[PDB]
Image (cartoon, rainbow, N blue to C red; front, side):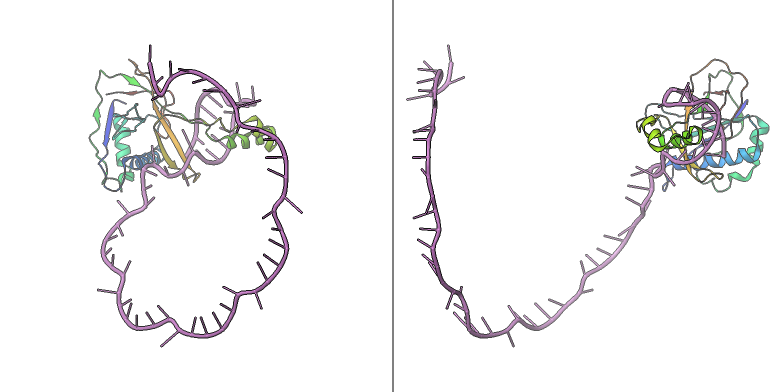
Length: 187
RNA sequence: CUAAGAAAUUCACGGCGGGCUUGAUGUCCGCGUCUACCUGAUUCACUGCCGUAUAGGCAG
């Protein structure tokens, strides 16, 4: 956790950086699924909260063995033309800590209507009256649009950075690099 | 401080009966429309699960 690897987005004359970010995030998700482990933290060094911008720089946080296992994986092939890869340097000691969390939303009422059909055996009009169409959740959070190998539907994954703390305790990490209770340093 | 200031047009009404517009007609010769383009920007806010929950989380 003491080390970090920094990825900068090369500007692209054919693609805006958002879909490049989505592609690389899917590649690192596949790399972490293949590699395993629960000590991989993500960071957005230039996250703009004014317009919910993802940013043009990426920071991944891991240990030395985890970082060399990640860079040894051949997922990096086919993406070197658009990114920078620095060195697994030690993170600065006086750094505030913040958490990253995947915030999902119930933006589609018909999914929950189908769910309550499978839970309470209600009819179509019962679910229509019980759940209006205005219950959609709109999030002013940065997001990435990806499709999964298990389910081919394209899903949107919101990423939100927590408040700055002064210390961090041990926690877990998901397959996306998002923390289920962990923290990443800010610098 | 205005060619300032003021004001009831209104009651009633049968327009109609009749009619052959028809004869004839050459539109027409000629014609280089070209050249050059990322539709796509996160544009699939989607599928399922824990929960009575629309309250609120979780899974790829």
